[PDB]
Length: 51
Length: 51
Image: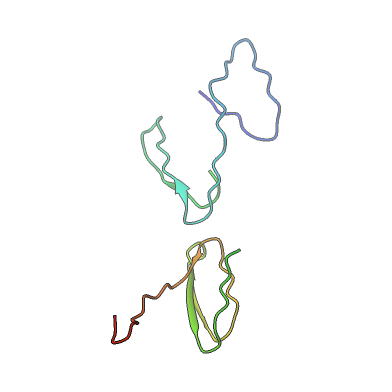
């Protein structure tokens, strides 16, 4: 699973398959989202800029 | 915007939680709260004898 993000256009090739939309979350300083990196488990609680 | 019109011989104390800074303005100023600025709500004694 890999996330393609940014100002681009995508056409899903026969090999790849779309899973979910992954809308961004707006966060300012002293606010964040409790993010659990399920590949490594570590919950980071990323705050500051949007994540 | 949330803006409080402070009386002349009065003081209102606020903190920008987004910016990690403290400021209190006395006198008759018009405070302008930043998106994470909050007021110093003061519960004060009143009533005929006291409360």
